[PDB]
Image (cartoon, coloured by chain):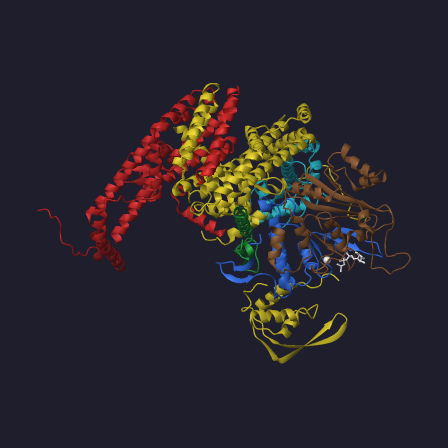
Chain colours: A brown, B yellow, C red, D cyan, E blue, F green
Amino acid sequence: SETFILTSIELYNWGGFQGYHRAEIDPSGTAVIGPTGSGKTTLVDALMTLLCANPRYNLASTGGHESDRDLVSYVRGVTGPGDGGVEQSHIARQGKTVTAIAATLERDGAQVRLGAVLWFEGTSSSASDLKKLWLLSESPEQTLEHWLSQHHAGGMRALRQMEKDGMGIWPYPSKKAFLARLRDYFEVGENAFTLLNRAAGLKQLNSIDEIFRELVL
Amino acid sequence: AQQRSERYVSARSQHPAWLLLASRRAPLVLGCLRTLFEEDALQALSEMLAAYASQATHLQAGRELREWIKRRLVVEREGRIYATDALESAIQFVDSLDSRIMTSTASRLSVVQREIENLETGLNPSPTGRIASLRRRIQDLEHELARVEAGHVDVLDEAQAIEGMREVYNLATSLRADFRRVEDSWREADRALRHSIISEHRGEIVDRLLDGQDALLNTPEGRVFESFQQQLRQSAELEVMRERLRTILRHPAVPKALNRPQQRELRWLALRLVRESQAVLQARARSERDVRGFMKTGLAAEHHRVGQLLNDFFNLALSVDWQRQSERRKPACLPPVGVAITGVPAIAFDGLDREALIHDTLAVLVEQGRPVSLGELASLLPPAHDLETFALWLAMAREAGIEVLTEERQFVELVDEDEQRWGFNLPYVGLDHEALKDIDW
Amino acid sequence: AQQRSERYVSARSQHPAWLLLASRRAPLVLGCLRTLFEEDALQALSEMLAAYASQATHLQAGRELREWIKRRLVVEREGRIYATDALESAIQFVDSLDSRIMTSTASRLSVVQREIENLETGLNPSPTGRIASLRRRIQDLEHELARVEAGHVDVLDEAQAIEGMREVYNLATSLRADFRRVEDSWREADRALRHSIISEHRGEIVDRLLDGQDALLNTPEGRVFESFQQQLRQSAELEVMRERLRTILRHPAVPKALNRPQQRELRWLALRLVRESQAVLQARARSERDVRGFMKTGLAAEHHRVGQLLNDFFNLALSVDWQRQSERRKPACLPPVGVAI
Amino acid sequence: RQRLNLEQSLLIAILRQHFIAYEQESGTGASQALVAVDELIPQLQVYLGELGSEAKERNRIITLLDQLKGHGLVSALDAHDRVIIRPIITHLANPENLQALVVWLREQVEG
Amino acid sequence: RFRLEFAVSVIDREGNNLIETRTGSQGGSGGEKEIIASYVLTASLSYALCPDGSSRPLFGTIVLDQAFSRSSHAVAGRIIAALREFGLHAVFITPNKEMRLLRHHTRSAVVVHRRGVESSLVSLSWEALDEH
Amino acid sequence: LLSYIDHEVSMIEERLDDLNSTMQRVDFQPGRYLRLVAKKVIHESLRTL
Ligand SMILES: Nc1ncnc2c1ncn2[C@@H]1O[C@H](COP(=O)(O)OP(=O)(O)OP(O)(O)=S)[C@@H](O)[C@H]1O
Ligand SMILES: [Mg+2]
């Protein structure tokens, strides 16, 4: 009808997954299954990072009492608390690297794509050294591989130059303007997405007054 | 005068809504149709018709639906049933017999006088009379301002406020009556266009229409709707109107005039109207796209010729004797099409299901019709998993209120897939169908 | 949900207009009724039914007429027949199936917005808002006057003019909607009052009501109609409105907007409205006079006793054998009244 | 496969007319031609005739539908008493074959 | 917004009777907390979307993690029924604890796998999976 | 202090009514459903002011 719904999800060089991966989701409601500790929560965390203004990674594990991870660990791809030694073998990728994610919403006679690109430059772990960029496309010819080709063929300016000659593209250097534009486009309340992220894994209710006075109103 | 009688006879003969009025089962049909608009329709119609024997079910419901579709009361596009103007007109007529908001009010007279004055002023092209009218209106407004500054703020009465609210609601809600009419006009125009194209097949017309990017399906209703929506696109006055309405709603006299649904409808006029207006553009676009796709097929001449040949064959088919088996079994001449091969060249999932077990146990209980203990029930219906079943039976017994005795033991011997033996020291229960016949699960 | 189903079943069972529509001979009878309201009626019905056998005329026409009288679609008072709301509703529904004036037009939207503003202003008791709105409206009118004096006179287009004219006709013709409803409400109030008096027959209530000069038979529709006619009695605005209507009547777009009957209807709006409004008060006065006459008759107790005695007699009459001639010829006990010598 | 007689030929012609009706008012999108048996019953009764009981006519129609399904023109009935007309009939009732069969039947009637 | 106090109440369908008033989710059992929290959160989310200012939602989807970790079958059935009645679209994430109900109420499945430190994602309908 | 606060409270009450209007459609345990209510309290330093 006139309601957008998620249709597919991309992933590239993110967390445990390496190389190029993608999954399709039927709009009639789908299930995700796998043995214990196989990456199920990773996919949803990657999806959630793109919407809320403050992610709560791996919330459902504790039932809603604590957070346990951060963006940098996902980006570099740690796979355990580690052993301790000269070579930190418990880290998948070191040095300069690139990560890119994308999501696709579809509606009858419509199609909208989101996504982001992040990268480092040298062997470092400071939060400030995280080069970030968010995107929002409308045309169908915009694909993740095109973005990667543009990045490898140039730099930040090369990526920004797409808007000058292309159409249906609006890069944002700051997440705040991106969120404002998204909310204006979708015509939703100011606290909808954070509410969704909070409702993803919460299993208790201490007092409804906090929920209404902080989220709903 | 007699022409009116002839037209009435024709209307009684033709118009589908009147035929639905003349239908015997009109109440149930109207109730079902009104409830739905707020395949599966056949299910709902049969379910409603079920507990109304009084006075087949599935067959009759299907026959009625197909007859109404042939009567064009509703339309079928791909897999969905859509309504026309006649349904809404009939529904309005039926539900208007209860309560109608009176129009012969002094407030309506005042509004009519104001609109008449506005029309008379607007249609005048004289540059002098307009200036004089503007001066007179400004003078009257200044007089009113002076009187108000004198301290003469006028507040209307309770009955006056109620009448004003009712008239405003009546006039406002009437904006949504013409929506289905535009869709029906577009569909009939499309059907006429397709009939003309197939009747003509000439490829020059198809090429010219495909080349032309001008909008097809031109009816006056489309232009009127376009103008209405174009003026509706200006939100500046819409915000003021919404604010005024919400200000009005907070008055003590509101509960005395309008019920809950009317207030709810009035609160969200603007956004609902905007969305409803948007909803028709997609339909127009899809209709145009389908027409263009059909035109690009280029099979109109083929269909015309095949229809002519089929008509000739069916004309010939009336001169044969279908009462003879020998003639009916006389082979014809048609080459085999799509001939297949000659058959051969001549050389930890699943777990447990609850519903099936419950239904089978209910069937056994009703067919036996006597109290049964666990041993006999296990013997008659051997289980796949020994557990997950005793617990279910005990839970049913406890929930139904049927007493269970624990002072005596019944020994049941079971053998699993891999041979071996197990012994269950169950207590005694007695199960009957009558006690548990009226509890959902 | 199911409540609406039950309500519609009851409506099919009850509403006389639906019964007339569900009749076999609905079209011809409806045409005859429309012709008449525009003995004698029964004769005309037989005349029309004569040359329409297709598909004893006097025998069946009277039966249908009397059934519909029982169905109350037509009211018979002394010897004359009058129409009610249901017949007019059915007539409107039938004639609306051919042409319906479009209602989703921009002009109606403008009227709705302006009337919303007017009512919101009129229901505000605060003086400061009134002053501010007055000044703002004066300023807007002054700006528009300045633009017009600058030479910006605007005239509606032919399509827009036709739209406006059709909307004006649609709104104007709505004034004659609920005339008969007041009459029907007064009739049912009369019946209810008579039944209450008979069920009571207490002479104190009748004497008090006769002594009291307060007008009885009061309905909310009566109050609304009274206020409407009180405002209507101001001829100053009526003359101006009629002059504007006459001025508009002479325009090139008139033939392309309305037909001859619509022009005729718009031509004599005021006189016909005054006539119909005056007709209601005479009927109400007759109803009140007849109510007072029936009350002054003072036979309610006698009629109640006679009704009770007839009920008892009819209850007892079900225990005899009516199949025997001898019992049917057994003389009764009744003294002669008005014997002829 | 076996040859085709006149009763099956008339049924195929009726199904071709149904397919034409379906194809005329069709646009972009995946759709199928489904026809109920009860709709087909009176049209074939017009030519063949009418049997005493509805059961007899229904059995005859089911037999004919099974005979035509053996040629791959239709499919099995669903739970709602409907059949699906395969597009292969379009090539079975192409105008050349239609003309040939019309001429042959005309010669059969005339003498 | 700090000058008000909020409470929830359970009212019987027929008639209008207070049956239980609550200010939170204290003192409950395992399943009760889960069902109450899910119900109130999904209702609040449904309101918080476009129908806040009326009209139908433009972005309808909701993600549940570790679905039905503590409840029984009937509670899960009620949850699914309510979620569908609210008129949204759901994606479920569960271990292999339960799959019958998912098969009964879904159409597509994604299987993830790990072999070493990599990962593999496969998507499929149920009909293809049934044949293995 | 008077106008802004009172108007905000009134708007909040109206919005809460709108929210609890639609809750009734969805069904809780059979024969039951939920409803949200609010009460007004005034306290703290306001009186002092
Ligand atoms: N921040 C992190 N630090 C270390 N290891 C991590 C981190 N994030 C994820 N992992 C690894 O990624 C895996 C956990 O991710 P997931 O497989 O999504 O967990 P999971 O899917 O919730 O497991 P289940 O099935 O829900 S119990 C483990 O192998 C962890 O060692
Ligand atoms: Mg977690």
- Choose between B142 and C113: the one closer to the eye: B142
Rendering coords of residue B36 (x, y %): 54, 46
- Choose between C326 and B399: the one closer to the eye: B399
Question: Ligand 2 shows up in which quadrant of the image?
Answer: bottom right
Most extreme residue toward the left is: C341
Relative height, residue E68 to residue D94 (above, below): below
Rendering coords of residue D95 (x, y %): 69, 32
The residue positioned 69% from the left and 31% from the top of the image is B297
How many numbered dots are placed on residues in this image? 0
Question: Is residue C278 shown left or right of residue C261?
Answer: left
Question: Is residue C193 shown left or right of residue B139?
Answer: left
The answer, for residue E81, to whether it is visible in the render is: no
Rendering coords of residue B294 (x, y %): 67, 32
- Choose between B141 and E37: the one closer to the eye: B141
Most extreme residue toward the bottom is: B407
Looking at the figure, which quarter contains the C terminus of chain B? bottom right
The answer, for residue B23, to whether it is visible in the render is: yes
Rendering coords of residue B24 (x, y %): 46, 45
Location of residue C16 (image quadrant): top left
Looking at the figure, which quarter contains the N terminus of chain B? top left
- Choose between D96 and B290: the one closer to the eye: B290
Question: Is residue D56 shown left or right of residue D3?
Answer: left
Most extreme residue toward the right is: A86
Relative height, residue C193 to residue C119 (above, below): below
The residue positioned 62% from the left and 28% from the top of the image is B216
Question: Is residue A99 shown left or right of residue F35?
Answer: right
